[PDB]
Image (cartoon, coloured by chain):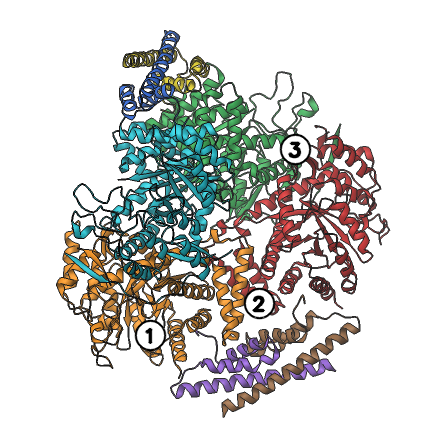
Chain colours: A cyan, B orange, C red, D green, E purple, F brown, G blue, H yellow
Amino acid sequence: WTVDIPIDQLPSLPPLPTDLRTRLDAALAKPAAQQPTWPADQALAMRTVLESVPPVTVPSEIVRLQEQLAQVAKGEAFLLQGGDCAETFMDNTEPHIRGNVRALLQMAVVLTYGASMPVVKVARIAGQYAKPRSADIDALGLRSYRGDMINGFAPDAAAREHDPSRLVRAYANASAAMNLVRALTSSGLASLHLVHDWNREFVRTSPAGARYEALATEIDRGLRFMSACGVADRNLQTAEIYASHEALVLDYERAMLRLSDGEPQLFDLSAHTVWIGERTRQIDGAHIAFAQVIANPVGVKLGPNMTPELAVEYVERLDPHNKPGRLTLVSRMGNHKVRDLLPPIVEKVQATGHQVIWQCDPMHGNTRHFDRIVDEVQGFFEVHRALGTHPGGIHVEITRLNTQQSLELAFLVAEMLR
Amino acid sequence: WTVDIPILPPLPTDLRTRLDAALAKPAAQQPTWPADQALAMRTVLESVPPVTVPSEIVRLQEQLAQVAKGEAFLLQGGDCAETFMDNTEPHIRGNVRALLQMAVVLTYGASMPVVKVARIAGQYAKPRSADIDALGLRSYRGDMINGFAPDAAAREHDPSRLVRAYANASAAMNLVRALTSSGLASLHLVHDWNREFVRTSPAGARYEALATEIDRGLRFMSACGVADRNLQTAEIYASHEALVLDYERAMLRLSDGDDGEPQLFDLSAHTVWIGERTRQIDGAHIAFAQVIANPVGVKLGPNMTPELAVEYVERLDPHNKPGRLTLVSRMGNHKVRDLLPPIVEKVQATGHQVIWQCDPMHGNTRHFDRIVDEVQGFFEVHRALGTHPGGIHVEITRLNTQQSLELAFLVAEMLR
Amino acid sequence: WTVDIPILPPLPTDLRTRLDAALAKPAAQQPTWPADQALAMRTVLESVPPVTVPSEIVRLQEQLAQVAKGEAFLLQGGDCAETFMDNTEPHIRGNVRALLQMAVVLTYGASMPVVKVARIAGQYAKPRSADIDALGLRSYRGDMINGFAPDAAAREHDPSRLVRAYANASAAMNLVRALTSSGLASLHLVHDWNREFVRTSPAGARYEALATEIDRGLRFMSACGVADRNLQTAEIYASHEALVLDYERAMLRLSDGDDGEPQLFDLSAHTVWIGERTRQIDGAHIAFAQVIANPVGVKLGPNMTPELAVEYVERLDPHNKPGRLTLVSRMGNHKVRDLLPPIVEKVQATGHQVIWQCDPMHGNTRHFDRIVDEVQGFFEVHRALGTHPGGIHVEITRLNTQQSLELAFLVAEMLR
Amino acid sequence: WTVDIPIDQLPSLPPLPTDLRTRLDAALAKPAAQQPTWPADQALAMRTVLESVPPVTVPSEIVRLQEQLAQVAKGEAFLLQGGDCAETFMDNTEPHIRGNVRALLQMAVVLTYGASMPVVKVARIAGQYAKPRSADIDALGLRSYRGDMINGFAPDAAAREHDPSRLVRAYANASAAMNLVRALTSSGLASLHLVHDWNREFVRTSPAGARYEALATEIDRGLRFMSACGVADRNLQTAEIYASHEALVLDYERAMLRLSDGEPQLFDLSAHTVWIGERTRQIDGAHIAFAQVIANPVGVKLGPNMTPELAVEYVERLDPHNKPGRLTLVSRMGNHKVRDLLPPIVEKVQATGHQVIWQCDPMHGNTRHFDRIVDEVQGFFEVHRALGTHPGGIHVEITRLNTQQSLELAFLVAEMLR
Amino acid sequence: TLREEIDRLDAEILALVKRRAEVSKAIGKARMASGGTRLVHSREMKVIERYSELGPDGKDLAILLLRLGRGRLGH
Amino acid sequence: TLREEIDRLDAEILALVKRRAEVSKAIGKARMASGGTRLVHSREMKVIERYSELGPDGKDLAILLLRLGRGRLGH
Amino acid sequence: EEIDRLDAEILALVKRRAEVSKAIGKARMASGGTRLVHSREMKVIERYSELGPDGKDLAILLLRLGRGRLGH
Amino acid sequence: EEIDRLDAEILALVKRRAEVSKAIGKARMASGGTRLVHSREMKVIERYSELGPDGKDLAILLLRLGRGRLGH
């Protein structure tokens, strides 16, 4: 059983300025890989609804993130990006969102201690509802599942058809999630000492706990020292978790564009930051052109086929104003390749004079699974130490790694940061 | 055009019994849609992310306790009715700004904190005295129930509007949270709007002295070393009339309350009130209010007796928790001075500490003068009894935004 | 009765050369005691704990830079002359209270920070135009030099008074620090004294509106969540006229200054000034001021020319450091409007940024009206030129405490 | 060569209230050990000067110390008391005072980290100018040196005569010192991370540094974590160092009495807290009677001849209102005796229901010297662990122990506090 | 003699302001006796506009006259 | 008709206040021409005491009359 | 005080374990494997738990000498 | 992987050093001395500095097993 919810067809706000729309329209005339195959008129109808809904994020938050990412780029902070590999509407619930917020804050406190510098927390949340696929036919002979913004997971033909109403369903889920993320990060749950009590319960009940007990205890003593010196929860933070997803479905991202400033600029207000995946980063494609036109900080996934030359081209396209932290280059080479392939990319990019964030994705390129994940982050750190560059952050998927494992990874990366 | 949606641990035994008993009582003013369709929609809402969280409701209760004790003032206001159509960022931003503007004026005049409660993220249902309106159509009952369009088809009660109401509510709340933690919620940026109002209003000369005094107070704060980062982030709470019990029961969640035991919280809002037409003492709405942990209000009109007011207090604040209950006086300007004092005296003699809040709209010589006269009479009642004039409840549509600002200036004077 | 006292790394070569050259210049108004006895006393003072520390002087310089740039106001005041006899806790506490009271009023009126500089912990020497007074006795030159008693023996210049001055100064400073970090320095406790003054003064009705407005501003701060713990601890700086060069040179200490290189700081005070009778352009006092890192002031009377004022600025602020130099106008109320503008214009054209401070006492129809008229004329001069009226320098004895408070209210009005 | 400085004979302020003076006069009719032998009329003259001088401390600071000592007594903070064994007028200079302030702050940051709770910092400063002596004739055949408030150190007859003008000379030195202590504790010197940089320089250059490097590094990482979480110097503290000395010369202490409050009370404003030494703690003596009448927190030195019964008598005399932290009992048994002698004292006092502070003085009762000092603090901790009582603080003399050693001791006591 | 006029000119202002306070109170009672409201917003703006000729201070004088006329708001 | 009187009563107040502002300015010029000070503190207290009969608001009216008379302080 | 001899021995064995541990790391990497292997570090830690709560600290210190610091 | 045998040995020697160290502590205390002696802990630390910067950490851990935690 399903229920139909009428999409309230409501009055338009003023259009975006004609000049910015001309630029956007030129950008989106470029070919776009991995796009849903729904009819353009239905897509247009759904975009028109989304053009007037309240945004998920607001410009001042994106400007603030940019400033914090500038510090990461300059070697004075570390980026933690993490969360669900794929969000689903079915699991977009309070316990699931709370679990992810908790895990991110737990990772961040360990990483802050190890890094001795602030950690910017970016969730894969409130929009991670679309993925590419290598084949349009899966192992059951069905059209491939492309995420809940596009079609249904259920193994049947009707569910797998590309349904443009899922654009509006994605927005509703995204804004409801983000509302809860904001509520949670402003509560006492997000208190540093409450967050770390969970880390100590992890050490106490995990089979691998003895490996992390010394560091968990050291962190606890740091927090108690803070408190003994008169530092209260009352003053700190309050916790800031930013929203990100892969900018994949351009119908959604373009509908969520809003105007803000010194000059008028388009911000993508579906998220704070977005990235462009390995299969949609064509240099002359629509995704890269779109990232070019928006003010948001952006990331590009770089795999083993990456050349240092193409990497410099992303820098020149995506950071033309030389704004530190505006562009993040996300390495996902595989633990066996990262030590060979990343260094010449890093050297060439560093010689441009631009300040990107170097972030490690140890999942997408990868004896045992966890050991390979850890080995790629290790290899990533080794490359940056040798080159004198900043190992700027990690990008991890929780499902891949479960929550307990991602927490272990934070402890091991904390040790690497020392 | 439609979106398609394809359709949990048990309550403690006592909470289930009490919730069931409350909802079995007669409920006035309910939509007349089919129970099976209602159940499908409630089932969807039972698993969605909440609009508010328990820790915020407990914090509101603490802040409202200060109002009840005479140490803070309650400002409640916003749209008379939110509509899906106007649930847009410019509209939401305008309401947040107006409430913040009114709050800064009222804080200065009260010389004490102001609790800010918006009619927002849920104010989608209204009661009607008649089911057939002046056009011969079934009455518009708000966007949670039916459509405003003057045609029969649009007026049919549509249970899918429960889910639409939630989507609209959570989207608005998300933005309210974003806006209140942005730099535009800064007190000095907020009061620059009040100063623009004084410059451009035709009545501005009446308020300029006070707006200038406030500005000098702000600049003084800053000259003493107070920065925006040093202040508390602006807090706007969400409220609406708890009218549609299908919606409120679907948004119930279990959490540990202020005394540590598991309690039911209505997570559709921080606080809700029960209106004149649904406050039957043995009805579902009052019984429902008795099972939830949220702070609540009850509207009291000109037929209220001191004895019935005490009964509401004893049923709704049985543990004597200051701030849990607000009594919202709406008597009309010609009646408040005569009818409110006996109610206040009887309630005060119980030892319970309610918030006395003035609703100068619904009981009401030009219209603005009547609205101001009721609030004036409300302050006189409390001054004479030695009790606390605790707050105001205003609606913007009739009072427009400019008038609601003028009223804040006038009430700030009364608070002196 | 007497106490008995039984009698260091070298300065950088350049600082020794410069210090020696400054002190070899002619010094007006110096005590006439024997050099060998002076040397013994300076030797004692060379090893004592300082009255102030360099980090505080550097912080004062930063805060004075804000005054010079038009973003803060300087309040300087306290006893016309401190005496050993009245160097008691009630007297010191009274002065700290009065200065804090004046500062809160002036902050509110200025809508910007007020830097508080007391004449305290060292104001023990004064110049005299005549060496024989009206009783035929050698003139009393303050307790650092001789005694106030009208007899010849008490008027002899006594170099032991250098050590007594230090003991009195450090004891007073200790208490000033204790008092300014106590709860009584809280803004709201401070302004309760202003409100008592308005209640009990015969002129109170003139100031009640402003005192009430200030109180509402304070209560507003508090209603917005600002607590005393959240504010900056009250900072009162120590100043006196740098008159007796034996004392000032004995209190010099070497420390790294604002640019990192070793500098000489006079640690007898945070800031010092040079008076009308000792400001000879090629004399020891000005040359001494050129060697110390402390912020300094120079008194400018009615015979000041625009060209000589520029010369002081170029000698005393050679690195163009805003706030390093204060020019203290004391023209008399009948002359300030005519004589100050050419001085201000010429100095402003240099590109240096001095603090312009009004001393309405020493150039001056009842006496209070003349004092107020000079400050009034000072504000008019600056309003006309577009320059900053930067501060006031007042003395309590003649102006009493109640009058000095009234003057703060009147100047707060001028600052609006 | 000396210089005579006339004592300005200045006007009196109002006398203390007649009722409090009647109580004080009754107290001071009791016999007082170890008092200077100067003439009563000269003493009276000097006291009269001191009765009208600005105080060294103020009542609100003493009330605040009391509140902080109440937390020590309740097991929620730790007391660090330390400084010069004896202050001299000759060494009462900026470098010497700064050195002591620095050392105390250095010790306190290490101890806070180890304790995981606030440390109350009490200097032996601004008044520690008098000591008792066992014999009135020293090894040179001269009258014994009793400290600069009483006589001169110089080995000659004239210097050794008891000179009541030294009461006023002591005050001048005390107030000048306290002025500098206040200035220093309000500067950036007192910043936690600046203070600990000195600790790291200690580890780096001390021959015993390797013993303390792990803990110094751990503390550094705690501070950097604080800073990374957004905690600035701007908000913390500012540092509070309290003044103490042995209340020995009753002419000085009585002259420094001032009135404050709910009822009128005498505060000794020569210091924040004072103690009564082993040789002047006669239960029916003037020193204990004086401590009875003043509002200040007080301490009593307890040596190896102490009985549990006499210790309860001090509690009943000196804490009649049962105010936690008003009374500190300072153990100085010797490392060889502390484990045997302290426990029955602690048990009996604990059974009164009063809440004293238990503080260890490991100096005055004591293979090698440093090992004995450490062993007594160790023994002290062992006694409290076994009894379930709070090891409340330490009282150390810097000269005994030099500065480097006292810092080592803080690291070792920090480890004991874990 | 100009000082002598200001004395008379102040006595006359004081008398008229006293009279205005009575006449204003009287209109208040009359409007309330007839079922109207003490305060009427449009009338307060008329008094303020009436004193605008005095400059910026005119509106402050007006508001003061309204306070003598009705009373403090909330009381 | 009481409303009609308040209209007249306000016209007369406005006229006298305008006249007082002129006469006050004139005394100011005269005292300054003779070498005196614009403001005289004792005289301001006399004006304030003179309006005390109006109650607490009397002193506010007085200060307003002094502001129309001399001007703003500092200007 | 046997006991400097006992320290001279454990020092020699600790130095040797570092040599052997590095040799294992070069072997696994030369054959196409990861330097660190999580399950082997848990085994070294479980081995020393007989010493009490300080066992794991010794274990982790022996791992540090063998496979170096993480991130370097 | 010799190497579990190497771990089995150093474990045995570490356990034995704890036994001997306690026996020294009882001996010194029975003869009227202090449990801890600072100069001896410096000697144990200097002994292990050949292992590098982790030497002192091992040394201090061996002292902890021998003479227990400070304060307990």
Distance between the alpha carbons at the discs numbered 1 and 2? 35 Å
Kindly identify which chain the residue marked by label 2 belongs to: C
Q: How many marks?
A: 3
Q: Amino acid at mark 3?
A: Arg
Front residue of D146/D1: it is D1
Quick check: D295 left or right of B336? right
Callout 2: SS: helix
Whether labels 3 and 2 share one chain = no
* Residue at 56 percent of width and 36 percent of height: D189
Q: Position of residue E58 (x, y in %)?
A: 58, 77
Q: Amino acid at mark 1?
A: Pro
Front residue of C313/A17: it is A17
Kindly identify which chain the residue marked by label 3 belongs to: D
* Image position of B348 with respect to A341: above or below: below
Q: Residue B341 bears which disc, if any? A: 1
Question: Label 3 neighbourhood size at 10 Å, few (<14), some (14-19), many (20+)?
Answer: many
* Image position of H24 with respect to E44: above or below: above
Callout 1: SS: helix
Q: Marks 1 and 2: CB-CB under 8 Å? A: no
Instruction: State the residue position of label 3.
Output: D166
**Occupied quadrant, residue C37:** top right
Question: Label 1 neighbourhood size at 10 Å, few (<14), some (14-19), many (20+)?
Answer: some
* Residue at 26 percent of width and 37 percent of height: A402
Q: Residue C208 bears which disc, if any? A: 2
Quick check: G9 left or right of C14? left
Viewer-side label of 3, 1: 1
Q: Position of residue F65 (x, y in %)?
A: 63, 76
- Kindly tell me whether residue D127 is visible in this rendering: yes
Distance between the alpha carbons at the discs numbered 3 and 2? 52 Å
Front residue of B414/D54: it is B414
